[PDB]
Amino acid sequence: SEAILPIASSCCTEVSHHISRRLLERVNMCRIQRADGDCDLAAVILHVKRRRICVSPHNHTVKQWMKVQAAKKNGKGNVCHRKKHHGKRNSNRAHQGKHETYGHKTPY
């Protein structure tokens, strides 16, 4: 444990931004950190047995993960969002899984 870069701090001043579920599924604790009067950055604090990873709440994979994790009846500790959307406008089976198009600014 080093104090040059304080690991012993409840907040997440840094994030990994984008993350995969194989890590997320290992998460036991989730907290939504908000820029308001808590800490100066909006982050998802994720506690894993080996490390505490901090990710961006804007991450699509996280929102997918949280729905799977929300299904836990034991308790919901590693879960923050219980819903990815209010619903989902999805397709049956002919889809991309996530048709995330980087909206091109100025089509001309």
Image (tube, rainbow, N blue to C red):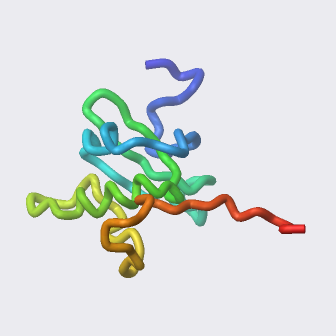
Q: Position of residue 55 (x, y in %)?
A: 48, 46
Q: Nearer the viewer, residue 33 or 95?
A: 95
Image quadrant containing the N terminus: top left
Question: What residue lies at 47% left-to-right and 38% top-to-bottom?
Answer: 9
Q: Quadrant of residue 85?
A: bottom left
Q: Nearer the viewer, residue 10 or 21?
A: 21
Q: Position of residue 54 (x, y in %)?
A: 46, 43
Question: What residue lies at 42% left-to-right and 38% top-to-bottom?
Answer: 53
Q: Nearer the viewer, residue 76 or 18?
A: 18
Q: Is residue 55 left or right of residue 65?
A: right
Question: What residue lies at 32% left-to-right and 59% top-to-bottom?
Answer: 66
Question: What residue lies at 42% left-to-right and 47% top-to-bottom?
Answer: 45
Is residue 41 positioned above or below 81 on the image?
above
Q: Nearer the viewer, residue 68 or 89?
A: 89
Q: Quadrant of residue 93?
A: bottom left
Is residue 40 positioned above or below 106 on the image?
above
Residue extending furthest toward the left? 74
Residue extending furthest toward the top? 2
Residue extending furthest toward the right? 108
Q: Position of residue 14 (x, y in %)?
A: 57, 40
Q: Is residue 12 left or right of residue 45?
A: right
Is residue 21 positioned above or below 63 on the image?
above
Q: Position of residue 39 (x, y in %)?
A: 56, 54
Is residue 38 positioned above or below 5 on the image?
below
Image quadrant containing the C terminus: bottom right
User: What is the count of numbered marks?
Assistant: 0
Residue extending furthest toward the front? 94
